[PDB]
Image (cartoon, rainbow over all chains, first blue to last red; front, side, top):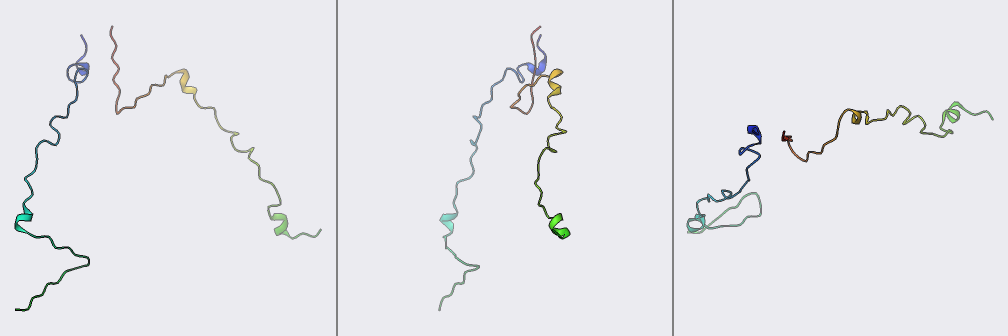
Length: 50
Length: 50
């Protein structure tokens, strides 16, 4: 006649991490639509002739 | 002879430590009425069989 706190609830229970980091995020797709340009200062300026 | 107050007031004297630890009351008087139990845990559960 063990008291409920020390029962299947807590005393008899094993922790498992099968659900961890299983639901993923949508795959990255920004490369297909955008291109990467590096920078090394506060801003970047672009110019073309015509 | 004929020493100014600063030289007399200056620390020609040695500094001891017999003052410290004089009133150091002996701890651990609670062991007579209490037992020390390590936790290593947020909480502890104590349940005995009858």
